[PDB]
Amino acid sequence: SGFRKMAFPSGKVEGCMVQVTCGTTTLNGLWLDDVVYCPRHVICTSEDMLNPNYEDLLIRKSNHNFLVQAGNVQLRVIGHSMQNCVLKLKVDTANPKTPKYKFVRIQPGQTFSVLACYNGSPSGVYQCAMRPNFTIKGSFLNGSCGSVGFNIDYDCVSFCYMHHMELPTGVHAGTDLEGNFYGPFVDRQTAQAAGTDTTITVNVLAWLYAAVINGDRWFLNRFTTTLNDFNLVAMKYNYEPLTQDHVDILGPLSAQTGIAVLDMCASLKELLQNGMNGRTILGSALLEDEFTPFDVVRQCS
Amino acid sequence: SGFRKMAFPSGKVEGCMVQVTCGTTTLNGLWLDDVVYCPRHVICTSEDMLNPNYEDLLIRKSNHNFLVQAGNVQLRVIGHSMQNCVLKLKVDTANPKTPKYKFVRIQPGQTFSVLACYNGSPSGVYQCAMRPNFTIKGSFLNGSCGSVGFNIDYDCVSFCYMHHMELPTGVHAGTDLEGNFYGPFVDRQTAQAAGTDTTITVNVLAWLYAAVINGDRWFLNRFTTTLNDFNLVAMKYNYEPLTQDHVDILGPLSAQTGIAVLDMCASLKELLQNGMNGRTILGSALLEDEFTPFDVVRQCS
Ligand SMILES: [Mg+2]
């Protein structure tokens, strides 16, 4: 029993964190095999922030301009290349701690653990979700760029995010491990704002199913709803539209509890209307949207 | 920016998790140097748990009856003894992944990271506080007994908790690493309940400081109070009394934000008496009490 926002054990990722220095800028790097991945903005100076020409800045660099430090040991850069917004530093040693891994680009609503790092040394681990507006509500201070987001599927580490910047609203933007940003963000210091954020409807529904599984039914009602009437209501509360894919994904949770997906949608329409009336669901006075249907099945079974 | 429930990186502790089997019972053990630590109830069958005699059950067990699995390697138990509610299995091999460590007993209100495991395999990590009633609000399913709690100071792991049981209200009970229970609990399958819990006042105040550091200032006011006046409010709303040691501990946060502890107490007094009135603090409609002053300073500075 109990429902916690649980992160993946960070160990397999800790053994990959290194410190990358270029000039006066120091950030984090991901050392997998003989390659260290990091935000390409590490090659920018006070002058190269509004309109950096990365290709021009990079052609002027030699391997010895990059200082990579894995723990106390200095790694030797033997090659460098750029792929989208990530810099790939070829090193003279393959990381002996390289776990089984893959790079995966996630979609909004997906959750992942973040190992926040400073100077290539891990600080903390926390659970995150990719918001519908392609930002993440993380916890990052200056020097955390290059910190990564991941999931662990049995023994395989799925790297899904690398930290690049904090937007003016205090939210975070980054790329997948191939350097492609999530959202319409760019690695430039120009004015860019996150779009309006919405609630991940499929995740709230899954967490309401997690509440039923752990013995709570106070919020259920005797009504049902069509998929279209649910969306007409939910979108008035800034909820993401619920698709037939979402309805299908909740199928196993619906079968476990005996409550149809659209009966649970009717209970969510009522919760939005009445609030909680001094009650909590799974120890929360708000409707939680950072637990996916997959996380619910994996945590509470 | 950003404030997240953050756990210490669990890598140093993952290298210590082993599976321990005794008959049908399989649970988790902590392998430090040449000793595996685990709950002493591993020797009990379901009938033995009704009223166990551990000294009697242990003398009738021999080294070969304990199956210790470290990954895919069998560890040979060469000795077995008991310290309070913890069973110590001396093994033939020292753990080469043993970090710099200490066994420490924490106080209620202090926080720690839990590495939840199943058959010596870590599955997740989460941060939690030792409740004033000595229980922990964790997330555990069958097979998690022997999962440990810890803090990391520099490169030293301070082990403080080992999971033993779940209480009928969903909360969890366990011991320090020397087998002494936190709370009035016994490792016997009998009617045991968690006492009435209270809110950790110094932790709520620390979290209000983190809210102010992150730009959430709506709850601040021109008023101040006294420790004596505030404690009458605390007692009424089931909050732990605020001592002078708590005000002293909050000193750096008072200085960094310009809001005295009794100035922040007048804000907490108003949130307790009048509520949040549709507003949230750090995306929460409840006053969060599982961040210590130190956790806030560590994450914000
Ligand atoms: Mg005040």
Image (cartoon, coloured by chain):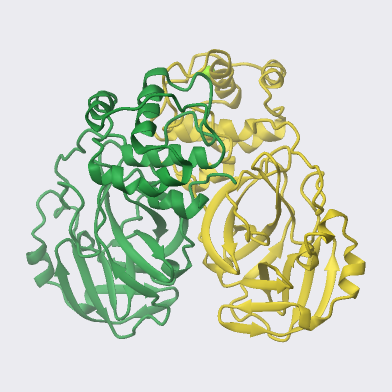
Chain colours: A green, B yellow
Residue nearest the observer in this picture, A239 or B179: A239
Q: Give the percent coordinates (x, y) of residue A32.
A: 33, 75
Left or right of B91? Residue A248 is: left
Q: Is residue A226 above or below residue A26?
A: above
Which picture quadrant has residue A144? bottom left
Q: Is residue A200 visible?
A: no
Residue sitting at x 39%, y 55%: A114
Q: Give the percent coordinates (x, y) of residue A35.
A: 27, 77
Q: Is residue A221 visible?
A: yes
Q: Is residue B240 above or below residue B51?
A: above
Left or right of A19? Residue B138 is: right
Q: Give the percent coordinates (x, y) of residue B95.
A: 64, 80
Left or right of B285? Residue B179 is: right
Residue sitting at x 14%, y 46%: A184
Residue sitting at x 65%, y 35%: B248
Q: Give the percent coordinates (x, y) of residue B55.
A: 91, 67
Q: Is residue B230 above or below residue A100?
A: above
Which picture quadrant has residue B260? top right
Q: Is residue B218 above or below residue A181?
A: above
In the rendered picture of this protein, how many numbered marks are placed on residues? 0
